[PDB]
Every structure is written in structure tokens, then in C-alpha cells.
Image (cartoon, rainbow, N blue to C red):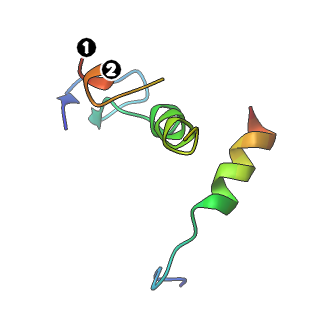
Amino acid sequence: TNASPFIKRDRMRRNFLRMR
Amino acid sequence: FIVEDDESLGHKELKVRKGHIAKLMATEYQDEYTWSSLLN
């Protein structure tokens, strides 16, 4: 499992820039 | 967080989705949603 000990935010902002 | 019991996808779900929080993220990093503009 990955279990999420830490997380990223702007990488996802960018992923939604490509998604939208 | 609100929940509708019924769902076309099935069992039970809270109404808010990934697109709304994506728009919230976009408005925060804009530097036009607010908390009130989610409330309305």
C-alpha cells in the first residue's frame, strides 16, 4: 500500500491544468 | 458536509465532488469561488 504519509499539491494543480 | 441518500451511482454519497475542490484550488492559486460562493 501507499498509506499516504506525505502529500503534494501543486503537482495536482498542474495535472488539472492538463485535465481542463 | 451534506449527503444525499439516493444516488444514480448507487448506495449513498456526499454531494461535493472533485471538480468543485479543483475549482477551489484554482481560485486559491489565482492569487472566483469563496466559502460563501460554495454555500449558495
Determine contact: label 2, label 1, CB under 8 Å. Answer: yes
Please give left or right for residue A11 compared with residue A3 in the image. Answer: right
| Chain letter belonging to callout 1 | B
Which x, y percent locates residue B28? 49, 42
**Quadrant of the drawing holding the C terminus of chain B:** top left
Residue B21 placement: quadrant: top left
Per the rendering, the mark at residue A5 is none
How many marks on residues?
2
* Above or below for A6 versus A11: below
Per the rendering, the mark at residue B40 is 1
For disc 2, the neighbor class at 10 Å (few under 14, some 14 to 19, many from 20) is few
Which x, y percent locates residue B35? 28, 31
- Residue situated in front as seen by the camera: B23 or A5: B23
SS at mark 1 in the image: loop
For disc 1, the neighbor class at 10 Å (few under 14, some 14 to 19, many from 20) is few
- Residue situated in front as seen by the camera: B39 or B34: B34
SS at mark 2 in the image: helix
Which residue is identified by label 2? B37
Residue at x 76%, y 38% (from the top left corner): A19
Give the amino acid type for the residue marked by disc 1 in the picture: Asn
